[PDB]
Amino acid sequence: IDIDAATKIMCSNAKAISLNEVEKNEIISKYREITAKKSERAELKEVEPIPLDWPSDLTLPPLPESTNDYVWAGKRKELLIIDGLSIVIPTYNRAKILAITLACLCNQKTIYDYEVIVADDGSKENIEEIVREFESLLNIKYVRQKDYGYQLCAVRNLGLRAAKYNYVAILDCDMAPNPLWVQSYMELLAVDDNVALIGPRKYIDTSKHTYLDFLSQKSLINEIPESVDWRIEHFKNTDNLRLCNTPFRFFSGGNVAFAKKWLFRAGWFDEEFTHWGGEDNEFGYRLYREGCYFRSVEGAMAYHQEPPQLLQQKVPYFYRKKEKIESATLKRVPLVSIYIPAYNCSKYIVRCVESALNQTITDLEVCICDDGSTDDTLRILQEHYANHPRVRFISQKNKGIGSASNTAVRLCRGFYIGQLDSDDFLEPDAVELCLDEFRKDLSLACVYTTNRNIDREGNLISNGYNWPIYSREKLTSAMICHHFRMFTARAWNLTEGFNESISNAVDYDMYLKLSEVGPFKHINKICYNRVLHSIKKLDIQKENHFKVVNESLSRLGIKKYKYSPLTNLNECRKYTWEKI
Amino acid sequence: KAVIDIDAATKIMCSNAKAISLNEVEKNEIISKYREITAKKSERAELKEVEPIPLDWPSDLTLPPLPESTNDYVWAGKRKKQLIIDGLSIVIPTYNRAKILAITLACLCNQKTIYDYEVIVADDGSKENIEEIVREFESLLNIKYVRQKDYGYQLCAVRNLGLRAAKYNYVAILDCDMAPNPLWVQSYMELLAVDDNVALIGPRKYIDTSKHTYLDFLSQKSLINEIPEIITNNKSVDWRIEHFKNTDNLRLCNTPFRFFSGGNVAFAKKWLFRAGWFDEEFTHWGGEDNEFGYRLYREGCYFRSVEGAMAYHQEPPGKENENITVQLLQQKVPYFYRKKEKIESATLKRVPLVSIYIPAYNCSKYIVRCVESALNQTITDLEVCICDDGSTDDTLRILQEHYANHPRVRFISQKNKGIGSASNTAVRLCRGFYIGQLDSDDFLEPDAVELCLDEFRKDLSLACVYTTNRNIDREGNLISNGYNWPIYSREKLTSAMICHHFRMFTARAWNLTEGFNESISNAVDYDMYLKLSEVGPFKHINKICYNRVLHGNTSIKKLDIQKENHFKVVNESLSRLGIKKYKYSPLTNLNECRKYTWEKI
Ligand SMILES: O=C(O)[C@H]1O[C@H](OP(=O)(O)OP(=O)(O)OC[C@H]2O[C@@H](n3ccc(=O)[nH]c3=O)[C@H](O)[C@@H]2O)[C@H](O)[C@@H](O)[C@@H]1O
Ligand SMILES: O=C(O)[C@H]1O[C@H](OP(=O)(O)OP(=O)(O)OC[C@H]2O[C@@H](n3ccc(=O)[nH]c3=O)[C@H](O)[C@@H]2O)[C@H](O)[C@@H](O)[C@@H]1O
Ligand SMILES: O=C(O)[C@H]1O[C@H](OP(=O)(O)OP(=O)(O)OC[C@H]2O[C@@H](n3ccc(=O)[nH]c3=O)[C@H](O)[C@@H]2O)[C@H](O)[C@@H](O)[C@@H]1O
Ligand SMILES: O=c1ccn([C@@H]2O[C@H](COP(=O)(O)OP(=O)(O)O)[C@@H](O)[C@H]2O)c(=O)[nH]1
Ligand SMILES: [Mn+2]
Ligand SMILES: [Mn+2]
Ligand SMILES: [Mn+2]
Ligand SMILES: [Mn+2]
């Protein structure tokens, strides 16, 4: 009835359960032996990357240049009103300076409408006063909340709630915008509301200028001298973030614009960031994982007028550095999330879930979906993991494997997701191995190992099928994405999730949808154990789905070819490309 | 030398509107045309053995009772998902009443409730220093201040502003002169926590706080319930209170939005996404209240007056400046206020009274006839919304060459997704209240709509009215007088598809249902009307007002199997009514057979 060694240690470290130095390390010792076995390497062979009979004129649409290739995103297609831009200006009483920015906003040269919401975070100076001073020159609104500390996040969310248009832009009160600021944003958002926009900043002393100066001389901003925005170099070197895999690191909250639909898809600014900051990188980290893009805007230049690291807990993707077990403590947002789709898995679920909790990597969680199990899977799940801090389940009506998967994956909170079916089990270092490949090529959408075939009793049946080198062309020919697969949250959110209509091939289908968004990496080691177990019509629909899935992949705009069967023999998966 | 026209009625309304001009000759031509084109009358079918309820109908079987009203929030409550009761965002529209606003805020300081609430003061460009008031209360209330420039009477705009800024899932609206009693917040949230599909209306009292200040109120939080009532512009009273008790707090009221006073209400914020926001077109004349309430109504929301959410209307400054609502709502609230008019006077309305929906798929040679039959109705206050299920023929082009600019016809084309899908899409397109069905290959009689309408008026509780029809060849050839079941009964319908064409229903009743079934290749109509039969009372009209075209001769065996399948399914699905002690099975398993038998479980 006990819980895994790791989770127990982590709780103790965080001092939430008492454990004397003798038990603490008797449990640590136990955790070490249980995760000591390493993975056995599978066997390789002289394989050729691209299949031999791969159509000589057929060309798979190129992948993106990086996880953040908005250009690549642009040329992607399939299957809408630009009313204006809502400009939220978080302000903590820097009156005269605010007026200056406001002034610079009156001189905007754009074709789009734009309102201005001054977000006063309980200023002591009378800010309302200077806003009225502009009521005629601007479609300006005024918003204020009481003073209860450094509530930068709270105010940004108030102003954002107040915003009336489908597009918003955040701009600190000290950030004077150039004359083509508004225009440079709307110009881009209009083309793709799927990419967040970042504006560079410069530095200037506005001390020798009142707001009156900027109003009559609508260009004085592009003149005053000046310290360089550390990001600017990083910008041109990565073709305006187009080649960045960590774009949220450059998402400064003083000047950015994006489609308001992202607030609801990814959430708002974390109001917990009171004594910290990095809420930008955290907010943008969430946009990132939810499929949002980032592009740095040249014309979005603004001037920062001079004034008169627990991301560790919320951003696993790039910041969080691995910690030792004796130091390890649970994280608010875990790094790894193993999703499990369970149905009638009474006798195997525990071994399954435990094989996951007992991993080299303890910074993870397990999310399960009870797909209307008929046996007492749910009861086992309840008396074993109900009050467990690293395991979460949710029940529903049996809607099939695809549906169970989606529910399973939307439940995940981590960045790296792993698939573990309720009847199979992992090796104590599978997550770690895949993690290593991910940390090595931050462009990767998926990394998969191989496996071995197991008996429903445990007995060894045989080593699993193993195709040594991955290639998009080999996957589009045969399911070579052996199990255990571990795919990035972001990549998944760039696809249509799992197919809830097919009765099988649900996996071949997913990794097919994922093989379009990014580069996969294969590891030739056995880190998974898959169990194997009276129809001839059910096998009919089985070879149907295998084929259906491969051509649904046509969602790559390919019509000149059809991945057709070489025979109508159930068990056979031989193919042939027929022209049209 | 040929040409193409647009129906007479529509040509005539645009003329009577001075939006278009016709010479007397041409106009008289079109009027008399309309006069004859709509002179016919539906022929009444003949009744048969009046057998109310099926004898084979179980003796231990009772269907859950229908609501005692379109607004029976009690009936709504009992029915077959946890929400997050976070807080209550009170939006207070304000304009130059600093001292009066102060008292309001003070009373909001005296709230005895177990729920978290925020106060958003929405200032409609007041000159008085409203901000100073807010700041003077930040250490007592979780208050926010939202302000917009002065550009005339912008009540609706300032309400919306505050609402967009509201952080909770629940919102309230209290005019700055409405000093709430101490139980105000609690009396609302208590109810909102139980059912968020019902808006709440609070009563008001008239008193003068003239010789008082906000501190007098923070000092003794009962003073508000002690200030004597006064006579406003024996004292004045909320004209709605004798109505709240006469209809079990609106529970028995059929036109509940008439009491939705924007000065003291509360409701889930989700409704703003469903019914919309406050129409910023309204003026200092008023009306926005009811019209918003009216939309809330057509989308499914229920109304309930709350005795515990009473507020006190503080007499205005005094330095302050010193009839019929039908006129104001007329154009935008068709439901109750709208009344018919004759052709030579009739004019187009902002929100049509009737919306005829059409699910069209490869109906190239019938579509125009179809649409024109709806446009040539005795009832001219009507519109047609068509959804083309991505047809293969030239349907879309016809729609375009014929109605792309029609003021009373609207359409949208998607990719084929079945009849069920197109029905939803077409209904979602409708903007009227009373909506009728018209399949693209059929067509109506010139008095169909009206007849149905006359029944709706007579009984505002009805969810649907339907007539009987006749069968047509693929060219207008009379085949036979379609099936007709004399009297309606929920029991009979659950036993047999007795809801024949033409069917009309309330946009609301439809919104109280779950829409059309998009996973069944057929039996869609049975399903839908079955979904409505559980929501309200039907009324059958024994007259042939619809012409049904029989084309299926081509019925590829298996397709006839599923058509049998789904038929059973629909009735089964009607299980969502709680009924578990029974089943509705196919007596014989002969394809075209429809006989049944109830089996126990
Ligand atoms: O380069 C960065 O990493 C940071 O630059 C800016 O911030 P910064 O110029 O460093 O700080 P301030 O200008 O002093 O404050 C930022 C904003 O917080 C607001 N603020 C400050 C204090 C307060 O109590 N409430 C409040 O809303 C100010 O109005 C201002 O708009 C951005 O606001 C940060 O989000 C960003 O992370
Ligand atoms: O073609 C597919 O969809 C599947 O092919 C193989 O899976 P396989 O072992 O053949 O099939 P199962 O083990 O029965 O199904 C995979 C998972 O779905 C769950 N499942 C299955 C059936 C069901 O109705 N509901 C449900 O949740 C199972 O418990 C299991 O965890 C792959 O290993 C799966 O990951 C992939 O989803
Ligand atoms: O069981 C049903 O759901 C239908 O049965 C009969 O309809 P029927 O004449 O048999 O079928 P159709 O005439 O082929 O289709 C009904 C309407 O849906 C449209 N439709 C049909 C097929 C489709 O894929 N999409 C689509 O929009 C058609 O144009 C037509 O107006 C009834 O007369 C219909 O009122 C009812 O909707
Ligand atoms: O230009 C205006 C005038 C009034 N109001 C608000 O509209 C509501 C109704 O005003 P009033 O009390 O005069 O309405 P009555 O009591 O006459 O119905 C109050 O919340 C006012 O603060 C407003 O927002 N803008
Ligand atoms: Mn700054
Ligand atoms: Mn399995
Ligand atoms: Mn008033
Ligand atoms: Mn038909």
Image (cartoon, coloured by chain):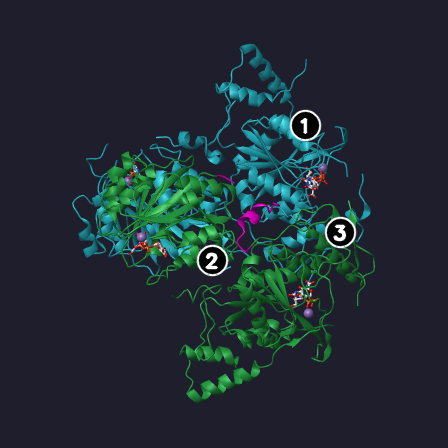
Chain colours: A green, B cyan
Residue B44 visible (yes or no):
no
How would you rate the neighbour count of disc 1 (Cα within 10 Å): few for under 14, some for 14-19, many for 20 or more? some
Residue extent of the magenta highlight: A66-81
Q: Amino acid at mark 3?
A: Pro
Q: Provide residue B319's location: percent of width, then percent of height.
A: 19, 35
Q: Provide residue A117's location: percent of width, then percent of height.
A: 34, 44
Is the distance from the Cβ of mark 2 to the nearest ligand 1 atom less than 8 Å?
no
Q: Provide residue A377's location: percent of width, then percent of height.
A: 61, 72
Give the residue at the far bottom of this rendering: A22
Closest to the observer: A91 or B82? A91
Q: CA distance from mark 1 to mark 3?
A: 52 Å
Q: Point out the tag, 2 or 3, that comes first from the N-terminus.
A: 3
Name the disc covering residue A286, or none.
Answer: 2
- Nearer the viewer's eye, disc 1 or disc 3? 3
Name the disc covering residue A310, or none.
Answer: none
Report the side of A166 relative to B180 (left or right): right
Q: CA distance from mark 2 to mark 3?
A: 40 Å
Is B490 one of the magenta-colored residues? no
Report the side of B26 relative to B53 (left or right): left
Q: Amino acid at mark 2?
A: Arg
Q: CA distance from mark 2 to mark 1?
A: 54 Å
Q: Tag 2, which chain?
A: A
Q: Where does label 3 land, which residue?
A: A55
Q: Amino acid at mark 1?
A: Arg
Q: Are marks 2 and 3 on the same chain?
A: yes
Relative height, residue A220 to residue B145 (above, below): above
Asked which secondary structure carries label 2, the reply is: helix
Asked which secondary structure carries label 3, the reply is: loop
Report the side of A213 relative to B10 (left or right): left
Q: Where does label 1 land, which residue?
A: B369
Closest to the observer: A266 or B183? A266
